[PDB]
Image (cartoon, coloured by chain):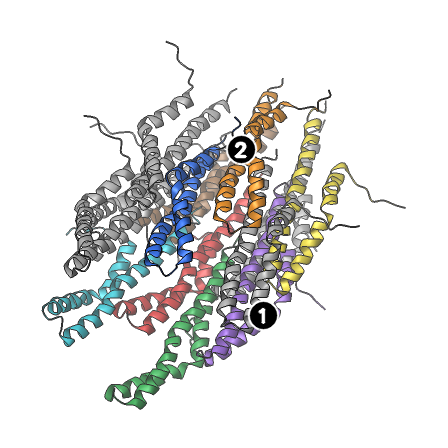
Chain colours: A brown, B red, D green, E purple, F yellow, H cyan, J orange, M blue
Amino acid sequence: MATPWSGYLDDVSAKFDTGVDNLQTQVTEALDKLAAKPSDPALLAAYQSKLSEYNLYRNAQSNTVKVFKDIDAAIIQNFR
Amino acid sequence: MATPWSGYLDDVSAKFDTGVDNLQTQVTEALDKLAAKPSDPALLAAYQSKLSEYNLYRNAQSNTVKVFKDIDAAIIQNFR
Amino acid sequence: MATPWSGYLDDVSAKFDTGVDNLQTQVTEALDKLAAKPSDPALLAAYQSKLSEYNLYRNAQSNTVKVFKDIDAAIIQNFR
Amino acid sequence: MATPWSGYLDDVSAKFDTGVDNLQTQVTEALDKLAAKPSDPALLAAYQSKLSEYNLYRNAQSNTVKVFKDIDAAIIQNFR
Amino acid sequence: MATPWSGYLDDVSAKFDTGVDNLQTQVTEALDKLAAKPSDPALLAAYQSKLSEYNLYRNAQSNTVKVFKDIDAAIIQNFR
Amino acid sequence: MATPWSGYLDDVSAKFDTGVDNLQTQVTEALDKLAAKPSDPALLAAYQSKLSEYNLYRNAQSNTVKVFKDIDAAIIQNFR
Amino acid sequence: MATPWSGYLDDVSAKFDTGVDNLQTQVTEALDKLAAKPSDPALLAAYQSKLSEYNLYRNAQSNTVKVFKDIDAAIIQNFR
Amino acid sequence: MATPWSGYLDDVSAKFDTGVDNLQTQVTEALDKLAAKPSDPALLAAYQSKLSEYNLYRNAQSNTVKVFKDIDAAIIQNFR
Amino acid sequence: MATPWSGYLDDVSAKFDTGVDNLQTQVTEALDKLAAKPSDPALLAAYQSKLSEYNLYRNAQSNTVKVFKDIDAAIIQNFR
Amino acid sequence: MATPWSGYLDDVSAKFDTGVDNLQTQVTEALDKLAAKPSDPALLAAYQSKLSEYNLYRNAQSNTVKVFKDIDAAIIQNFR
Amino acid sequence: MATPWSGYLDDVSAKFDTGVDNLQTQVTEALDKLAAKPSDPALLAAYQSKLSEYNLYRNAQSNTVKVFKDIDAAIIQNFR
Amino acid sequence: MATPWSGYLDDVSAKFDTGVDNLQTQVTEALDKLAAKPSDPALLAAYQSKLSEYNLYRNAQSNTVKVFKDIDAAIIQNFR
Amino acid sequence: MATPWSGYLDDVSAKFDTGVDNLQTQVTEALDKLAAKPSDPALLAAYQSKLSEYNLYRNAQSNTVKVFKDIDAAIIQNFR
């Protein structure tokens, strides 16, 4: 019944991850397989393709949170 | 009813493969046959011809995905 | 009769895209064809030529919007 | 109604073979006959004459495909 | 009355092709004939001579476009 | 009698171009000729030699303007 | 009972090596044997085949670690 | 129950050898016999015929592995 | 009285050609004569000897210009 | 009696050039001679050897000046 | 008690030579004898047989060292 | 009794060189000998083997120092 | 009393030539004699033997200088 506290920026992170929740799992499993056969073109292409997206999984995630935090700073900058 | 998640760059990879989905199968079967008779001019010519295309199956595939990812980086570079 | 809201920077994006609205379609169709025959010099040259322009379709687009936003920040920086 | 996939370089191979589709059959039948009477000057001359052409059936074939693939590499070398 | 959109780099490609528009046709027809008689010295010499030029038809074409795109990048690199 | 407005940085661009006003024309005409005969060593050498200079026609041009703009920013940074 | 400290990127390296832990041993033993008889086609083929994989044992290993470190930098880049 | 590790390129080597696993044995036994009677036309013809195939047993084998490794390099070349 | 514009790299090209201005003419005339009698040992030796130098007439020419352009890039790389 | 003004970074450039004042002259004269006989191994070796040093004549020169300018920026960055 | 320093690639060279340490001596002594009687079929066969192996004594040696150095470069290429 | 001043990065350079202090001497002496007999396979193999290590003597040396300097910059970047 | 300036890479060239200063003279004199009697086995053997070494007089010379220049580039690549 209890629910851990989550702020707005927390929610923003969740909102982004919602659409790419599977992305992490896919690229992780692609890594797991590729580790067994690094020389597999199929595993290389699949992993790298999903990894270039996983790059934004972290980058774009933190970027959007920053901006939503930046508009927070903008408001409290005028906190008369 | 469920469908695995696929990003834009994932879709780009699929879009390329769509037109050369058979290419992989053809050159694989050509390899399978050539393995039996490597000294067959017919199997050599067919396999090598389709293999020189299969070279782009991987190369050109990853190239187009990179570019579509590069314009992604270009945009988020200006992520004010 | 109703018209979706559009800001100045929105208009700037539209103004850029206006002159290259077809560019996206051309390079997309070039990709669609190239996918079928990646090994076609004609499709490679056409696609890559239009793709190097499509690079600016995203890059230069976001660049001009940034600048028009930067002069916005410059003004409100002096928002006494 | 269905048609097996064929790339550009595949088409190049077909384009060459089109003009020498019979060459293979002729030199094969010449071999078949010569096998029966290797000591026949007529079969030797005919077979060897068509065989020296069959030499290009494979050589020149793969050469032209290579070049058309080489200009493919040239283009994607500048795949910015 | 309508005219398909063409960018600067598109125009650059056209400008190059303008002077060698016939080159492609000549070497294609040379291939078509050579396919019929690969063992013809006349067709071999003519085709190969025009093919060594057709090598630049693709290579030099993409090279000049790259450079004109490179000076584009150079400018927008200073896009303050 | 009327003269279009030109700023300092505009003048800087003009000052650079003044010394290489012909450069653009020379390399353009070299391109025009080379397009006709790409396989001409003379046209290749002349064009490429002037093109490597034309590289700076754009690069160095925008570089000097940037710097003169950078010292502008430096001054107005202290615009008390 | 004690366990040496290992970071995430350390774990990433281990995760890759897990699937190719034997690869190193195989190619090392192949080298050891080949050293005795360099002129053995069997040892050459086996060693070189496993060596071309061992190329990725180091290359692909460090590549994946870099990327996982790159997304680390991406996050701390927004470390407000 | 245990199985030695094998990569993709390892599998490629095996896939080729699968179709010519007997080739090695045949030409080896042909050598063994020929060694006893080098002057036997039957042993010379049989051995040399199978040896010219054994030439590809090594050559074509390593060639196909190289290519499958080359497309591996192509992918990781774009390992952003 | 008027003199066409020439840059530094233009001057570099001229400086090289200065010492081999005659080389081009000599090997061209050697070609003209050889064309009449290709089977002349004297024309073959003279032409080929001067042609192997004419190889550098283009190669070494463009090489030195590149380097002088490379040190140009090196400087403007530090164009603070 | 009059002496042209020279700043610190000017002095830095002079300090570097002091030790390689002759380098420029040597490689220039080597070029002058090589231009006459490009096919001379002695002129090629001497010129190229001194040219690879002349590469640093410009590169390393501008590098050291940059650094001495960078520590200038570092100081005035704290110009309270 | 003192031991000269040896790097990894040094060790790699030693590891190869270990298995063919005698090869050099054998082919050297075969040369020494053959020098006395070049026309000896026995010395020719023995020397040439061991010389064709001595070919790899140098070639394959440097090849393996290169590769082990290449994976060194691969790692330090990602030396963030 | 007096000791020249040495910073941390100085110590880092020394720490690296400590393990390869002999490397420089070995490859220098190998060069000295090779200069006398460049055509000696033994001197070529030894020198080149130690030279490929000497490549890192400079490269890897400066790399590690850079990184230790980079973490210095990282700290003083937060020098509040 | 005056001594022409010489850089490190200059010294490297000299260091190599030191051990083969006579090589050039020997093979030059061998050429001079051979020119008189090209059909002399003694002059052919002597000249060709020293010429195959003179091949490295230029090749190996420039190779070692390149490497010593390459480690120069490696250092200044980290010229922070």
Check the picture and name the quadrant holding the N terminus of chain E. Answer: bottom right
- Name the mark on residue A33: none
Indicate the amino acid at tag 2.
Ala
Identify the element where label 2 is drawn. Answer: helix
Question: From what the image shows, is residue B40 above or below residue B6?
Answer: below
Q: Say left or right for J63 vs M36.
A: right
Residue D21 quadrant: bottom left
Please state which of the two labelled residues, at mark 2 or mark 1, is closer to the viewer.
Answer: 2
- In the rendering, at what x and y percent does residue E51 appear? 52, 69
Q: Do the residues marked 2 and 1 share a common chain?
A: no
Can you identify the residue that label 2 sits on?
Answer: J60
Residue F68, compared with residue J42, is above or below; it is: above
* In the image, farthest residue toward the left: H36
Disc 1 designates what residue? E23
Check the residue under mark 2 and report the chain it is in.
J
D10 or M64: nearer the viewer: M64
* Crowding near the residue tagged with mark 2, few <14, some 14–19, many ≥20 C-alpha atoms within 10 Å: some
